[PDB]
Length: 69
Image (cartoon, rainbow, N blue to C red; front, side, top):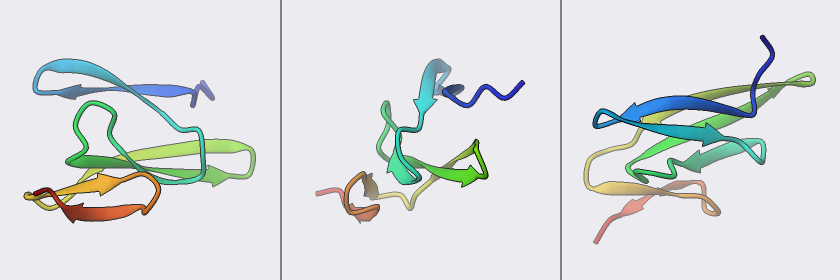
């Protein structure tokens, strides 16, 4: 199953979808406290949802975690 359009995850019990439009790390739609790394493997997409440090949030364009304040 080479389905890489969108993977489903659970944020606080609730289901959310993760979709990658570009190759690179982007925040999590539901909760920006987490982000997903979108990587290309030839013509296949691999995604991984990692949480950032508490107190900070991930930015899509900057591609890093900024202080949520």
